[PDB]
Image (tube, each protein chain N blue to C red):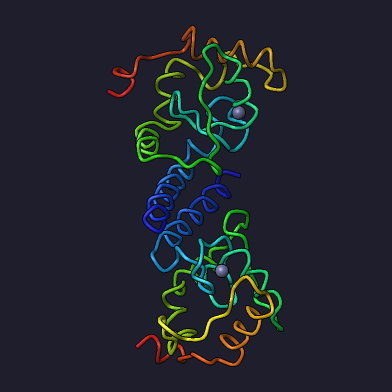
Length: 133
Length: 133
Ligand SMILES: [Zn+2]
Ligand SMILES: [Zn+2]
């Protein structure tokens, strides 16, 4: 459908507005490369390797392909209200970019433990209400 | 690079602005389905099957994948000044959508002859200077 097409392409335009924002240009979890997936659980943009590790959490985070998913209006709007800068202030609100503890990202076991500390144990976490203000 | 990323994502945002315009939602040549390629020779949005036939013209038209090409700023701006509505007024300026001669698009030989009439012999053509005014 053309009406279907119209909304689909609008969502992709909105998506590419977001993928060009500076914090969204690098994976939220490793900061080492460009994102290929969105992590819908928290509203971040992540790379494939980190997406694989996020699926190893329990419960696992929900990742969807940037290029292949047909995102809904609800999902696009959630992402607009989140993204990597908003997420940084929450999940990494206490993290110091110079020296806070990061894994060797070539190691899946260490990346798992790190993602657990980040999201489950909330080692560097500032609650969203505070983070926003 | 992040600066590289920024321009790349900007171009994709600009591209998706165009792919959502009503005339761009259908292949410029067959009007039968959604476009997957841009025809850079004329500035249109076309489907895969028509792209295959466009490559059979001599000289052939230059088609590039919507999803896989890294378009340049120059290319994006050309497309912004063209697209399927602008192209309709030129290449189909004399064509009647109710009854002008179209091929069975399931037939490659007939599609070739049609594209020759459209682009080479200019059967339905209005020059761009007139078409614009
Ligand atoms: Zn990553
Ligand atoms: Zn076509």
